[PDB]
Amino acid sequence: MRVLVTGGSGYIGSHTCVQLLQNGHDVIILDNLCNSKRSVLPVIERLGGKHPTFVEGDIRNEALMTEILHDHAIDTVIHFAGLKAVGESVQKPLEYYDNNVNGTLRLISAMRAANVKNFIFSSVATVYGDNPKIPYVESFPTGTPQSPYGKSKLMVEQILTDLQKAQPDWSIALLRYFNPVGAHPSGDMGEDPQGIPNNLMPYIAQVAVGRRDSLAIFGNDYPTEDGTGVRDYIHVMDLADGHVVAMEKLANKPGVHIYNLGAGVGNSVLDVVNAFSKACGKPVNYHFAPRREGDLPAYWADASKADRELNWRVTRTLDEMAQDTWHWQSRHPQGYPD
Amino acid sequence: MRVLVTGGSGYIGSHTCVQLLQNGHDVIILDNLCNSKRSVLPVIERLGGKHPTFVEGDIRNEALMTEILHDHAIDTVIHFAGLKAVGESVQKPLEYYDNNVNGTLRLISAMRAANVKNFIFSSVATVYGDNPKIPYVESFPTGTPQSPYGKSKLMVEQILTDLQKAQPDWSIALLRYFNPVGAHPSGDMGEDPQGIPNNLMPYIAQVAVGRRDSLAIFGNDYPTEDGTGVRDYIHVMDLADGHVVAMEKLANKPGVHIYNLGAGVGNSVLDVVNAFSKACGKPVNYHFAPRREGDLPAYWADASKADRELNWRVTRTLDEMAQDTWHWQSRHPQGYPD
Ligand SMILES: NC(=O)c1ccc[n+]([C@@H]2O[C@H](COP(=O)([O-])OP(=O)(O)OC[C@H]3O[C@@H](n4cnc5c(N)ncnc54)[C@H](O)[C@@H]3O)[C@@H](O)[C@H]2O)c1
Ligand SMILES: NC(=O)c1ccc[n+]([C@@H]2O[C@H](COP(=O)([O-])OP(=O)(O)OC[C@H]3O[C@@H](n4cnc5c(N)ncnc54)[C@H](O)[C@@H]3O)[C@@H](O)[C@H]2O)c1
Ligand SMILES: O=c1ccn([C@@H]2O[C@H](COP(=O)(O)OP(=O)(O)O[C@H]3O[C@H](CO)[C@@H](O)[C@H](O)[C@H]3O)[C@@H](O)[C@H]2O)c(=O)[nH]1
Ligand SMILES: O=c1ccn([C@@H]2O[C@H](COP(=O)(O)OP(=O)(O)O[C@H]3O[C@H](CO)[C@@H](O)[C@H](O)[C@H]3O)[C@@H](O)[C@H]2O)c(=O)[nH]1
Ligand code: NA
Ligand code: NA
């Protein structure tokens, strides 16, 4: 199929693009490069074994969006573009609402104009809000995210829902991601954060590579097996795969298809640390710190639905998540070249 | 004060502007005229006894917004602009999200750019969602509105909240309106809907004036005193007044000040009908129809807070609401001139 992948040069999108090309789809990436570099493009092509067309631009640019859509005869759009730094969203709410909420509305408005009606949205587990019931099931009603970032995702999901209802021939997937980690097995593509990484894995990776002193473990008094926070880590390659599948199986299938993308199991901060130490051949340095603001103690996905309906499930392990990360981190300590 | 009133030429805004001028404030109205006419301007000036500067434009136009804000040295902004037809929002979700959500974000982004930090937002009771607890109190947590229109208001309230938190010197009032009705006592300004009116009052008014046959009463089996739906009707003049007060007393007072704007009492469809029959000197024709989709049986505001904190409360009665409406309807059956 002809697919436009916004945010295509970012973390999850690049991996997604590789898998997409591998499946012989025609890929058009649209990214504004606020959190990615042009240097990843050649890697995508290489690893994907096919050329993806790149367009520098902003989802907020309705007209451009509309033009692309038409120019490339797109059949479906995978929307990864946006801002996602939680803490920062607290400090800069407008930018999040603008990039994410207005960003998506401009994009879907362009889609409407161009007659495109198949969409895949990058959502988040946070939409479940403070749910005591874990694992989290798609049949649960959403709650209220604590950060503007989370709010923004929930808002988009709602907008998309209403849109579908009003334009019923639309096929829209709301992919609720849990905690993406890992890197392409080649060790030549992976997550490349700028500055202090906010997620656990990359932070650990930075400590291991000698860039950081110690990992601060946000709280050790949770009502968890080891007192550290528990999450549902999912390898970026599995995520990528789930995207291809969702795109291929839901294209032209009217409705709002919601699926939790996770391994369906939880792992502690300690569990992750240990896996990493093992992967990089040395004990990762860490210390206990106070709980982070708004942090939940533990949650993970119920991924039966995706299994059942899309025949999709994770195949990579936690060790692999760690190994792949270390490989990329270690082979390219400066990440993507400027 | 110097105040920018978006949506100033509309229903609630025009009345608000009159009251504002009467209090000697400098008013700049910004409206795109999608649901109002230039013909109301001269009426505002007349009734307000002072000239308000008018600017035709769209809140979505950040740059313009920013320019106005600066050009006019605005001190505070009253934001009434947006789309509000519930049913239509179900049918055209994008336009609502765009006008309301993106619309407000562009406006507050312009405010930020111009250094303006006092805002008043037109909110809705629907934000309380399906709350069994009535009357509705500001201390209640919000729920989930059933229409994109309602969702859009809730989204804005959230965005504004986050913004305030990140820019703490901002003063933002979230005015939750209940059911505005009525008209300026002069009978020369009032609500001028185009096409089939969606609210009860105007519809009744149209029946009375001979334009409509019968009023359809949406359901007569509610668990209410008379089986008809109950609401908190509030005279547009009271609403207007509450806006002036809120603006004058909250300007430069950091925080998110939320207030329910209602009379604090409920009235049935029948109650309203009867009041109107009385006002126009003839029985209003009506019939019982099935319940409307998503209609709640009864709700009204708890307005103690505004009383307590702003010393504000309604002064107009239901009869006056009816009388004023009929007066405007009857004196200007074609509404505002093209
Ligand atoms: N990474 C996670 O843990 C996590 C968890 C759940 C949800 N998500 C979501 O998944 C998506 C992808 O996340 P990611 O990890 O790849 O982050 P990322 O930063 O790597 O990917 C986002 C990309 O989109 C681009 N972009 C940002 N705003 C844009 C705009 N207005 N116009 C055009 N391009 C724009 C950035 O340049 C970047 O390449 C995001 O929408 C994110 O919110 C990620
Ligand atoms: N009327 C009600 O019962 C009710 C109940 C609760 C909330 N509200 C809200 O109160 C506000 C005022 O409502 P109203 O009854 O006066 O409606 P209205 O239609 O009379 O007022 C809205 C005005 O804003 C203008 N406008 C619309 N979109 C615009 C845009 N993008 N840029 C610039 N101007 C734009 C329209 O031309 C119109 O003059 C709205 O935000 C509405 O959602 C009204
Ligand atoms: O330096 C660090 C970083 C993380 N943690 C802990 O590690 C776990 C995971 O932290 P993080 O990677 O920040 O995961 P989450 O907090 O759960 O958030 C991610 O996963 C969510 C869905 O699960 C999405 O909403 C977000 O976009 C995404 O960043 C949590 O227990 C954190 O307490 C630490 O102890 N120290
Ligand atoms: O032709 C009609 C119109 C209305 N009604 C009834 O009259 C009452 C009020 O109807 P309406 O004016 O549509 O009031 P609401 O449905 O309560 O909605 C208004 O008030 C809300 C807050 O109270 C805001 O969210 C909306 O913007 C606003 O339009 C309800 O019981 C309706 O069932 C009828 O029976 N027939
Ligand atoms: Na429809
Ligand atoms: Na701050």
Image (tube, coloured by chain):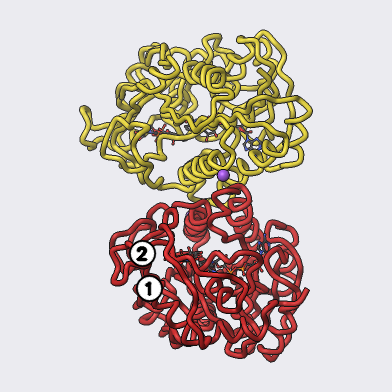
Chain colours: A yellow, B red
Of the pair A289 and B106, the residue shown nearer to us: B106
Residue A177 appears in view: yes
Residue A280 visible in this rendered orientation of the protein: no
In the rendered view, tell whether residue A48 sits above or below residue B220.
above
Instruction: Tell me what residue is drawn at x 41 percent, y 83 percent.
Output: B313
**Above or below, B2 relative to B295:** below
- Above-or-below relation of A327 to B49: above
Q: Amino acid at mark 2?
A: Asn
The residue at 35%/21% (across/down) is A304
**Horizontal placement of B242 versus A17: left or right?**
left
Query: Picture coordinates of residue A292 (x, y %)?
Result: 35, 42
Look at mark 2 in the image and give the residue it sits on. B220
Is label 2 within 8 A of ligand 4 (CB to nearest ligand atom)?
no
Give the mark count: 2
SS at mark 2 in the image: loop
Q: Could you say where residue B187 lies in the image, as x and y percent from the top left?
A: 62, 87
Question: Tag 1: residue type?
Answer: Ser
Residue A259's place in the image compared with A58, above or below, is above
Quarter that holds the C terminus of chain B: bottom right
Rendered residue at 29%/60% (across/down): B132
- Residue B252 in picture, x, y percent from top left: 53, 75
Q: CA distance from mark 2 to mark 1?
A: 10 Å
Mark 1 highlights which residue?
A: B268
Choose mark 2 or mark 1, whichever is in front. Answer: 2
